[PDB]
Image (spheres, coloured by chain):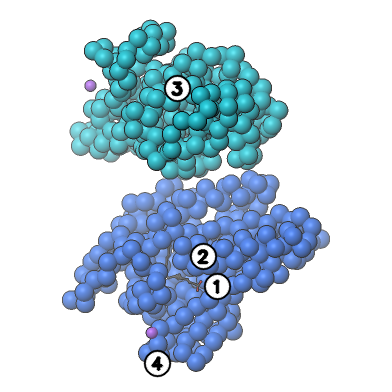
Chain colours: A cyan, B blue
């Protein structure tokens, strides 16, 4: 009985193995830069997006998926539907997925559909989708999957260091956080348990910030041998491999992987950004 | 051989007969003050004597949490691992005292595995967390693994209650954010927030329809009820507890359920006729 589908909004990256699996499906967000309106799918190559961001003087804007396209993704032959979305504190994607479930039941009746508020972004959503699959392979019931994945979400922590925080700041995703000292100061950012962004540390220069971020991850992680560590990078794979090396010096994980940022992740992480989740 | 672990629960958390007979569960008592009378909340305090004293006293009851020194002493024993389950940190100093007791322990003695769980609940909410600790230990998990699994359960755990008399919680500052209703026979359906505070979930006219609405609230929030234990605490109204149990069974199936009489602390704040439901 593998009658299930894992729906993830487009911010959550897919590894090549997940793309070849068939059980993972994306629901794409929208991206708007000046007078260009794009859909965050696999037809939007990262370089063209980064080049458009670089030329546009105006900050990029994004839009969550509509409830109707969530509902359409629920309507299929799979018995159990699991939805993984951006943090509800950072995007309307969660509320839209929940509304799509209400629309589905009005048009088609009851179905086992659960929407997971990742309280995170990017590879945070990826790891949750992988956790759903792991639970399904272990033979859990639908409600057992929900409980175990919601526990993993509670254990999961997100961290990131960017070169350019302006897109998150201008789009209202950094409210409360204090902003200009040394020009090479790099804040180490992270999630809160509620799914908002906070500042965890700071360092002058990228090399020192990556070390401090590695320390922050290691200071919070528990039972790391049971967990997969994910790293998303925006056009800086050698920086991603260095972060992986720093983290391996500090704790042992079950496994780890590195992925390129999705369209939404690229828009908000910007050129040179690094996101770590475990 | 020494016991591998002990679960310390403050006296608000009721023990089932099976837990009372298990030396792996141990209470740390709170204090109860009603007019000129001071009681330790332990098994030697009869609920009827407490209820009769409350009924006669025009003065509202007062309570006190355990001291950090008392918690520290409870940690110093032959059991290897110590788990502590306390009242919600937002409703009592019991959690802060247990954490301070741990800090004092590590300063005075060799390092020991001690973890304090903020239940963000009360009464059988603490009971079920203590049972979950035992379940995780029986599953063979490590200390860190037990801690992480129990904290996940705590986030899942929701508390609901309907009382005949909310005055003790109100007078003692435990309903700070809730608007009080004017006195036909409207009964508010109260419950926990994820932070461990009390909120009003619903309201109904009469006790019978209040229990129905509470049962609806429990059913609306519960995840994977089939694997969970549902607990019902009642203060001198066992038939009301069995009716609530019946209403919940109409809405979802659980692995098992139990009913217990309220502890001393739970009795003081739930009062005669109170009902508490946790799953
Ligand atoms: C709570 C932890 C968040 C970690 C953020 C990591 C940095 C960049 C990843 C992309 C974050 C995107 C957040 C804003 C998405 C808004 C999309 C929309 O609804 O328009
Ligand atoms: C957060 C959910 C709370 C549910 C409350 C259920 C009603 C009665 C159970 C007893 C509650 C006791 C709370 C106050 C305890 C204060 C003890 C102290 O003096 O520190
Ligand atoms: Na559309
Ligand atoms: Na008084």
Determine the CA span between mark 3 and mark 4.
Answer: 68 Å
Determine the CA span between mark 3 and mark 2.
Answer: 45 Å
Sequence-earlier tag: 2 or 4? 4
Residue at label 1? B65
Residues behind callouts 3 and 1 on a single chain:
no
In this picture, is A100 found above or below A194?
above
Depth check, front residue: A210 or A49: A210
Label 1 close to label 2 by CB (< 8 Å):
yes
Which element carries disc 2, helix, strand or loop?
A: loop
Residue at label 3? A164
Mark 2: is the Cβ under 8 angstroms from ligand 2?
A: yes
Closest to the camera, between mark 3 and mark 4, is 3
Residues behind callouts 1 and 2 on a single chain:
yes
Crowding at dot 1, Cα within 10 Å, few <14 / some 14-19 / many 20+, comes out as: many
Determine the CA span between mark 3 and mark 1.
Answer: 50 Å
Residues behind callouts 3 and 4 on a single chain:
no
Label 3 close to label 4 by CB (< 8 Å):
no
Crowding at dot 2, Cα within 10 Å, few <14 / some 14-19 / many 20+, comes out as: many
Which element carries disc 1, helix, strand or loop?
A: loop
Sequence-earlier tag: 4 or 1? 4
Kindly give the residue lying farthest to the left in the view shown. Answer: B184
* Quarter of image, ligand 2: bottom left
Closest to the camera, between mark 4 and mark 1, is 1
Residue located 51% across and 65% down the image? B87
Mark 1: is the Cβ under 8 angstroms from ligand 2?
A: yes
Using the image, tell me which numbered label, if any, was put on residue A80.
none
Using the image, tell me which numbered label, if any, was put on residue B87.
2
Residue located 50% across and 92% down the image? B36
Is A227 on the left or on the right of B104, as rendered? left
Depth check, front residue: A16 or A21: A16
- Label 3 chain ID: A
Residue located 49% across and 37% down the image? A199
């Amino acid at each position: 009985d593998m009658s299930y589908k894992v729906i993830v909004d487009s911010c959550g990256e897919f590894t090549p193995e997940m793309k070849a699996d068939g059980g993972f499906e994306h629901v794409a967000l929208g991206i708007q830069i000046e007078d260009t309106q794009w859909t965050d799918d696999d037809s939007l190559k990262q370089e063209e997006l980064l080049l458009k961001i670089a030329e546009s003087t105006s900050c990029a804007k994004t839009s969550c998926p509509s409830p109707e396209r969530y509902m359409e993704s629920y309507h299929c032959d799979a018995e159990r539907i699991y939805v993984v979305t951006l943090s509800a504190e950072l995007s309307g994607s969660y509320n839209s997925a929940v509304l799509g479930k209400n629309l589905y039941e009005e048009e088609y009746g009851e179905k086992q559909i659960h929407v997971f508020n990742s309280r995170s972004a990017s590879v945070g959503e990826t790891l949750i989708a992988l956790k759903v699959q792991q639970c399904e392979k272990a033979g859990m019931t639908f409600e057992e999957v929900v409980e175990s994945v919601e526990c993993y979400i509670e254990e999961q922590h997100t961290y990131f260091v960017l070169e350019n925080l302006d897109t998150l700041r201008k789009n209202g995703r950094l409210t409360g956080i204090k902003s200009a000292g040394a020009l090479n100061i790099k804040p180490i950012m992270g999630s809160t348990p509620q799914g908002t962004i906070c500042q965890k540390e700071k360092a002058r220069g990228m090399k020192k910030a990556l070390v401090k971020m590695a320390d922050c991850v290691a200071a919070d992680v528990v039972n790391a041998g049971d967990k997969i560590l994910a790293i998303a990078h925006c056009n800086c794979e050698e920086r991603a491999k260095e972060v992986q090396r720093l983290l391996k010096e500090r704790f042992a994980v079950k496994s780890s992987f590195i992925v390129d940022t999705s369209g939404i992740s690229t828009v908000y992480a910007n050129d040179g950004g690094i996101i770590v989740v475990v």
